[PDB]
Length: 147
Ligand SMILES: Cc1cc2nc3c(=O)[nH]c(=O)nc-3n(C[C@H](O)[C@H](O)[C@H](O)COP(=O)(O)O)c2cc1C
Ligand SMILES: Nc1ncnc2c1ncn2[C@@H]1O[C@H](COP(=O)(O)OP(=O)(O)O)[C@@H](O)[C@H]1O
Ligand SMILES: [Mg+2]
Image (tube, rainbow, N blue to C red; front, side, top):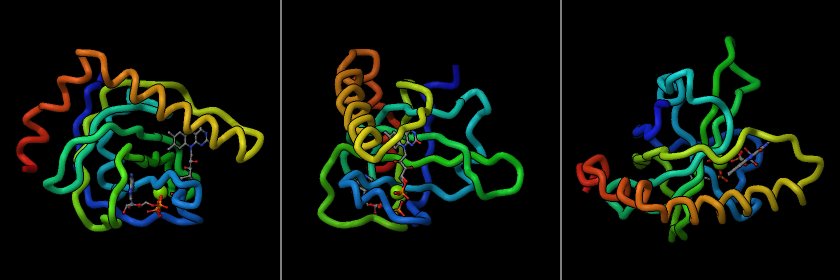
């Protein structure tokens, strides 16, 4: 209902061990950005398009979850871009267009099942983003302003 959702934010570090350890880096936005999501953007896994600073637009998956740590029930958001970056981009602006919903959050009983799930979400996102209604969002002026 609030898709496609467009937002931009500084890329910031997270806590615990980064998902770089899984070969699947996940970029965070400051709390200010996540707080401005409409409530109807429920938790779960979404897919869409992203660029960093003035770079090209690439396919991405976003995880929207509950934060265990802040007062009230604050959400969290983290984006994995399906593009190999030559270096990190902390502090740069990540521009995102969230275009579709993949699945609700799920509980997994091992890292094996978690990693397999994430890889499957990525492969499914790549397929869904080829649909003409989603492929066109790559060309949105939203992304053209950043170049
Ligand atoms: C596409 C995608 C889907 C995810 N799905 C789930 C999920 O269904 N359930 C869950 O508990 N964690 C899920 N995660 C969580 C990541 O494994 C977790 O947030 C990890 O700690 C990344 O944060 P980090 O940068 O601190 O490592 C998902 C992550 C991604 C990228
Ligand atoms: N494909 C990519 N998608 C998301 N982040 C990437 C990607 N390639 C490199 N990065 C870098 O990885 C960082 C995320 O790594 P991660 O291990 O998840 O740590 P953290 O969540 O604490 O920032 C991003 O802030 C960014 O600088
Ligand atoms: Mg991360």
